[PDB]
Length: 50
Length: 163
Image 1 (spheres, rainbow over the protein chains, first blue to last red):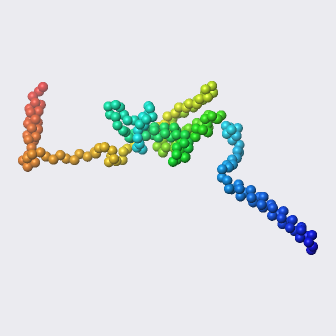
Image 2: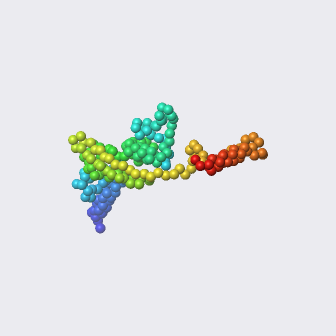
């Protein structure tokens, strides 16, 4: 081994850890606000569901 | 048979009655009770009554929006059947005018009539307790026993002679 790899393993750990902070954070705030209400329109639309 | 204060069908205020018998009245006949139970249920807009957010009708969904007549009729016809004593709905003439943008429907509802279970809480009693005798009648007899016999004799004397 050499210090050049220690400066490389850190990059592998840092970037990978950054992924959770993105995905894991978004779900946290999405659950911290109950005002938003999602809806889905499966068929229905043109028969007066407009 | 749901009892409640009577609401005047003509004005909407409490039915205090005619000027000769002014007072307060309770809805007794099932017809009158159901009438006002439907009237209040349809007159209160959904969510506008405090202490109960789920009561009322959601007029805001339809009024002011381009809506399909068929969808509205279903909701109108569904709210009626929430009462447990509704037998059926006979006819339904839903019509819509596009010029004035008004909508007006007609229909009738059929409901039976029940019994009163108990009169203890309402007014009168159904029994016929006896009346105490008067004077020395009890210990010595009654004169009516003579009067009825005399009348029977007189009517029998009347019968035999042809008339």
